[PDB]
Length: 97
Length: 97
Length: 195
Length: 49
Ligand SMILES: CCCCCCCCCCCCO[C@H]1O[C@H](CO)[C@@H](O[C@H]2O[C@H](CO)[C@@H](O)[C@H](O)[C@H]2O)[C@H](O)[C@H]1O
Image (tube, rainbow over all chains, first blue to last red; front, side, top):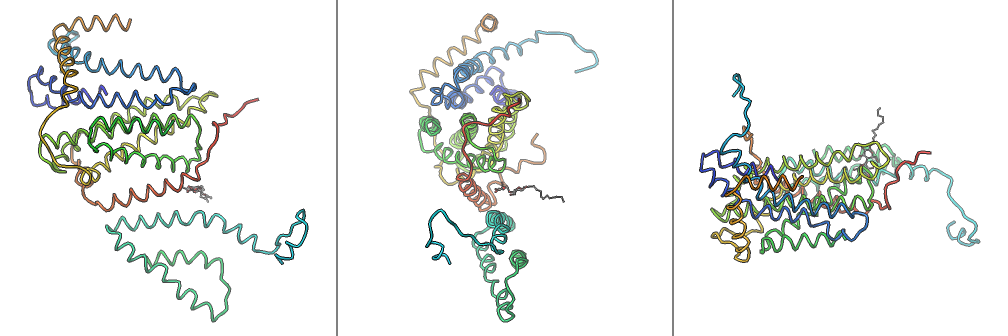
């Protein structure tokens, strides 16, 4: 999912549009699909959750999926724009781009 | 002989001891294997063509070839040979070609 | 339980697009099932609970990919021209990403399918199931979506969004703007949470 | 990276009957094979003793 998002972001950014509006449109365009993705991921294991065999794994899966998705929605945008507005690290190489 | 066998206590049983057993055992997997290859070659043909009409058209020639295989066999009174039971498939392939 | 999972994913796609659009995708789902079945046949991998659970997981992932592809297709065609070619660009564009993500997931699954321990036996089945299912699923999504669309899909329309999700969109955009207001705060929260 | 290829869409749109027949044969094959699949409780892990 993270790869899908980064690909969608840098997809149209090749045009050099406003990074703010670029990421804004990226999110506004990937909002609906990611929802269904998380749904299909979390769900499916619900009917078998009653089965004691696939127990803790089912709960852990449905939990981690929702968590990772929510952050994929809010965390990475702020993180990427922060890393973009200014390069935090250093260690410049004089013989490399 | 079957009726005779039936006319006897159930605890007893009769079976053949000739060659039919071996012939059937040999041709056993044949029946359970050849149709798959038939569909395989059929799809293979469909690759070169693009319409089921032409498919059935050329397929009509395949079974009709059983005319000579028996016309040139009845007067000679030659028993149906196993080798022929095999070669007939090659005949199908070449005629379809 | 298998049929139950199938019907829940079915209603999911139903309420997702509303129209009988994703329903054709659901109809396309059994295809990969029969394919993996014949695969197991060739490999004699019989059925058992473990494999059934693996089937559930694989079906969810594959239907997810197929549905997102169909969704982007119908959206790009609806917002613009109504034509198969008015979607061929969407195919040519988002094709590679599907393959990438799918292969990455199969890679993440791989580990469980390599231990020589006594437990690796039960895991071997599910590993084979997931792998074959996912691969055949991607090939099916990229090789069947065209006809299914060209024959059971209406033309374009004008942009509009379900107002019920309007409030949800309000909250989402608002929280997005707020998260952008203080980026360092989000980093602090993430750090404390993970810790 | 979309260099010298991307014929997936067109070729898919073309050769319609081909994909149709492939789908049909695959479906029937899987269907017939399903009956002769085999059902068992769980894999028999090799006991070592
Ligand atoms: C001289 C060197 C070679 C010496 C002898 C070797 C002969 C050929 C190699 C033997 C390998 C056996 O492989 C062979 O197993 C089965 C034979 O019933 C075939 O058929 C198998 O696969 C099919 C499709 O999945 C299924 O419909 C069959 O039920 C299944 O039995 C395999 O398609 C074939 O690959």
